[PDB]
Amino acid sequence: MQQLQNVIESAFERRADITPANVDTVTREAVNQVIGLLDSGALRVAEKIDGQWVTHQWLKKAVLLSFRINDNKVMDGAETRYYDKVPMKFADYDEARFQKEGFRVVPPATVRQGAFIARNTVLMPSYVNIGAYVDEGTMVDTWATVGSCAQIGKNVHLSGGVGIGGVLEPLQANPTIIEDNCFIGARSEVVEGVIVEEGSVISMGVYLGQSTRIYDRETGEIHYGRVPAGSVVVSGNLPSKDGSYSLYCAVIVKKVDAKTRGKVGINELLRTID
Amino acid sequence: MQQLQNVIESAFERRADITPANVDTVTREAVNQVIGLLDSGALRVAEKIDGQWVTHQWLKKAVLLSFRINDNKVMDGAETRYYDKVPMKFADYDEARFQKEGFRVVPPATVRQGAFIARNTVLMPSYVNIGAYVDEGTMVDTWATVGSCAQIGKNVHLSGGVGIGGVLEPLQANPTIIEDNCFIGARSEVVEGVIVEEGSVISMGVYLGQSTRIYDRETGEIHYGRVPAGSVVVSGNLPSKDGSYSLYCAVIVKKVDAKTRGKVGINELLRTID
Amino acid sequence: MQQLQNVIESAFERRADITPANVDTVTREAVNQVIGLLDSGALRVAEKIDGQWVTHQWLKKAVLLSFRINDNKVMDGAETRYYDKVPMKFADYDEARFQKEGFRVVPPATVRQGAFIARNTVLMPSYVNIGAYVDEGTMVDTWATVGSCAQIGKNVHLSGGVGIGGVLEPLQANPTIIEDNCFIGARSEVVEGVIVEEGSVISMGVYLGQSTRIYDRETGEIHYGRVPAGSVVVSGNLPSKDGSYSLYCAVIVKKVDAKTRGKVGINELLRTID
Ligand SMILES: CC(C)(COP(=O)(O)OP(=O)(O)OC[C@H]1O[C@@H](n2cnc3c(N)ncnc32)[C@H](O)[C@@H]1OP(=O)(O)O)[C@@H](O)C(=O)NCCC(=O)NCCSC(=O)CCC(=O)O
Ligand SMILES: CC(C)(COP(=O)(O)OP(=O)(O)OC[C@H]1O[C@@H](n2cnc3c(N)ncnc32)[C@H](O)[C@@H]1OP(=O)(O)O)[C@@H](O)C(=O)NCCC(=O)NCCSC(=O)CCC(=O)O
Ligand SMILES: CC(C)(COP(=O)(O)OP(=O)(O)OC[C@H]1O[C@@H](n2cnc3c(N)ncnc32)[C@H](O)[C@@H]1OP(=O)(O)O)[C@@H](O)C(=O)NCCC(=O)NCCSC(=O)CCC(=O)O
Ligand SMILES: O=C(O)CCCCCC(=O)O
Ligand SMILES: O=C(O)CCCCCC(=O)O
Ligand SMILES: O=C(O)CCCCCC(=O)O
């Protein structure tokens, strides 16, 4: 949308000099518009096109700028109080709205405005940061975190204590992406624009960043940055040349199967009743 | 209790066809009764009998059915709002009740109805899911999670970020059980009906599921599914046949002792003052 | 401050016999004063002097005693309720105060009274326990935990799901300390009075306690209890004498550099706008 994209990459340029006071209602209204698009899935930080994921860097820019253009305001907690600049997504909703939007929100699950939550999802108590996208049928288990701009596919299981890297701090080039039908094991972490291809299964306590060797015991091939579709990954270590010690790595132990499928399936009864 | 057990395994059968509208007050009232029993420790998903743990599969069924029989309702958060079908355990309590019930609840700790919290326990901010049982003197540290139906013994220390596997999603046969006097290290995960025998000490960052080899460097014996009473467990790796790489495992490095005891003890001063 | 220090080590002595009812307003008022000092950074559990960190054991004592001298009171959550004895730090604040105090508090971030939060910090939803100190420019990412009495330096990045060991349960001699300009990777844990020297980078899923070997592949030197300033640490394993298995350890793979710096930097735009 040029009418927005234009006013946005304009200000980004002066990012360090804009402030909640010296900013022009022009740029203010836009960033506000661009944020509202993201909040509704109408727009999205990243997308797959021609079998390639592509980042809309300028939408990341709008997210960054929301922080320069808005001011902190006190939020009345019950027993305590908050002071921040990003509104609560679900604060205006009524039952009607929740009813039509079709996902479930378990307290005290929390979502920031500018994040997209699809139909038939379940948010156990967790966190969804600004500009992120969570597709249909997905579950975000307890204490899990969907980082700023992260892309979550359909029917994905993010187990408890799972973290999906953002792009705000530390600043990142690309968002983290989990393709459809992936299962992420408890307390695992996926960061730095790593891509998990669809139908993959990451075990518990597995940590993947750009420096993580993803080793295929079968091929002897070592990957970096992505998990080939349909893989089952678990933690391991590779040894030093002198065999003096070993360092962490992610090992692809096999391709997903019936046995694997029996342990990682989604529970439809937990989903929205039509 | 046949009068309940009967009406329950009846509906479970038609699980996918019951809904918050087409359900008969008969089945509704029961599931509601069976849930209230669990909420009070009067009933419990699993129990030890003749030195064996036994699952009451039909009580798991009632838990599953609570999700088909009830409807989501909006929950008024302070700064935000929720939409879910399982009530907050502590929402009706007054000081009187808390006073007699004898445990401590640190905000923003959250418990679902149908979960049993014993006397003299301490809940740092954490999560206790439906149908779970937490015995006396136990502490659940910050961001820890007690999964649906999990069984937690007396005087147990679940450190920060510790996760205890549930049985809802992914669907499990047996609950996860931690026997009395066990200490679980920070950020560790115990899932898939694995049993931790009493007085055991699991270090930090240890992950145990049914596929996890629990290795005894002493005996050379490898366990699966349970931690022998009085063990001290830490993370390790076992090597491949060709020595080309190594995979994660849980190593039993020793039996608990004075040295160990000095690091994992409970702090009575933190407990309820009589 | 002798006038306080005196009345404090007096009662600590009778710790198990004091109670919220049999305690003298003298000792009550003090502990209350000593707690208020800590809440304001005026006092602090530990400090560096002559290039050595030193614990004020008697201030730890006051923290312990706050638990014997105060009584639990019900806290009104919105949808639920709490029962605890330590007040919410930010419950009395108004915008004016937040404005002058200069940090940001993202809901549902929670801080206990008696904890020091510096200027220009950012608390994503997380936990800061009593008696802890968080210095300037620091960020505490989502679901992170700053344990009781822990010391956090300036410009530190505690990533998501990171845990910093406390001293309450299990009872500890010294607090955990993170020096200035340190970066802690996602889901990592630092406990038992271990010290991380300034400008160090700990990767993801790294767990450090007193029994953790911190191995320097370069020197062959093994550390215990501290991370030498400017180190980059990642998980690994060291092998058994018979090569029968391997056990977890923290490996110092290199000294921090430009490459490293590009991945772990702070985002000023996220900080307080002057
Ligand atoms: C990845 C799987 C599913 C294992 O795959 P499968 O069962 O299909 O395979 P398998 O035949 O058992 O394993 C094949 C090879 O992989 C190895 N292997 C598999 N999983 C392993 C693991 N976790 N650790 C070590 N090795 C593992 C086997 O040893 C074997 O060795 P060889 O091939 O050499 O012989 C499991 O380990 C896993 O990650 N489960 C996830 C559990 C989880 O995180 N649940 C969410 C809980 S959280 C929740 O529900 C609520 C509570 C909470 O919030 O915490
Ligand atoms: C398991 C223990 C207690 C260690 O047992 P001990 O101290 O009795 O034994 P030890 O003599 O030191 O160790 C015996 C053998 O086990 C090995 N060993 C022991 N612990 C190890 C560990 N974590 N990593 C690697 N190896 C370890 C030793 O190297 C040694 O090797 P050899 O036998 O071959 O010579 C410790 O490692 C541990 O797990 N501590 C838990 C800390 C924790 O999680 N605290 C909660 C923080 S959470 C909190 O309080 C609030 C903050 C928050 O919420 O995060
Ligand atoms: C430590 C670093 C920064 C890596 O250091 P560098 O990039 O400078 O070094 P490098 O050249 O890539 O690595 C040098 C040596 O260290 C090894 N190495 C480095 N990092 C490693 C890792 N994580 N695992 C295994 N090995 C690793 C290399 O293999 C290499 O081997 P050789 O030397 O032998 O060749 C990275 O691994 C890391 O920890 N990143 C942190 C990401 C993170 O936690 N972000 C926060 C996400 S949380 C968030 O933002 C919101 C979402 C949420 O809340 O979860
Ligand atoms: O400052 C904020 O409000 C957001 C910080 C997010 C830190 C992790 C991320 O990059 O998502
Ligand atoms: O749908 C819910 O409300 C509960 C899901 C729980 C997921 C983990 C478990 O099996 O405990
Ligand atoms: O009882 C409490 O309120 C605090 C317990 C803290 C447990 C972990 C720590 O030592 O910080």
Image: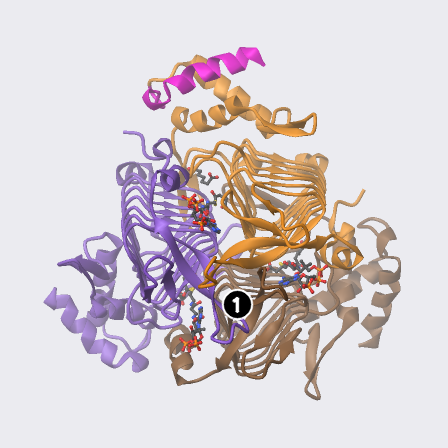
Chain colours: A purple, B orange, C brown
Lateral position of residue B267 relative to residue A188, left or right: right
Residue A79 visible in the shown view: no
Quadrant in the picture for the N terminus of chain C: bottom right
Q: Name the residue that disc number 1 marks.
A: C236
Name which residue lies at 29% across and 38% down.
A102
Q: Residue B78 or C205: which is nearer the viewer? A: C205
Determine if the C-beta at disc 1 is less than 8 A from ligand 3: no
Q: Residue B124 or A2: which is nearer the viewer? A: B124
Lateral position of residue B179 relative to residue A51, left or right: right
Name which residue lies at 32% across and 75% down.
A21
Q: Position of residue B150 (x, y in %)?
A: 56, 37
| Three-letter amino acid code at the position of disc 1 | Gly
Q: Residue C197 or C100: which is nearer the viewer? A: C197
Residue A55 quadrant: bottom left
Q: Position of residue C134 (x, y in %)?
A: 58, 72
**Vertical side of B150 occupied by C159: above or below:** below
Q: Residue B69 or B90: which is nearer the viewer? A: B69
The prevailing secondary structure element of the residues shown in magenta is helix
- Residue lying furthest front: B242
Quadrant in the picture for the C terminus of chain C: bottom left
Q: Position of residue A62 (x, y in %)?
A: 25, 68
Residue C46 quadrant: bottom right
**Vertical side of C47 occupied by C68: above or below:** above
**Vertical side of C218 occupied by C101: above or below:** above
Q: Position of residue A49 (x, y in %)?
A: 15, 59
Residue B195 quadrant: top right
Look at the image and give the residue range highlighted in magenta: B1-21
